[PDB]
Amino acid sequence: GNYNYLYRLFRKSNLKPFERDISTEIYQAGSTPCNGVKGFNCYFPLQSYG
Amino acid sequence: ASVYAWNRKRISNCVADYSVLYNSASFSTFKCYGVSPTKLNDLCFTNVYA
Image (tube, rainbow over all chains, first blue to last red; front, side):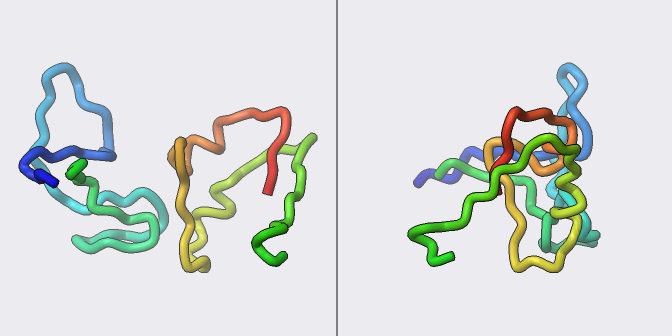
């Protein structure tokens, strides 16, 4: 796998046209307050296809 | 059941709120595929199965 190229799976809100977002914070998908760490429906939103 | 002959229950003629299920961190996992968990509370179906 090459891992140079990275993907965001989820976000708090949709991008406006040419909105740009570098932020890496853990995404709360459900009932777990993330506070900077993963958990039950709390996920790191970044990915790569390898 | 023994997983080779897994139980199927047909679900019909009813209103659904799947967040009553996935909000609870009581399970060892709750994951969703093809569609994110939140969206399932908007949907309508002819049949549902557990």
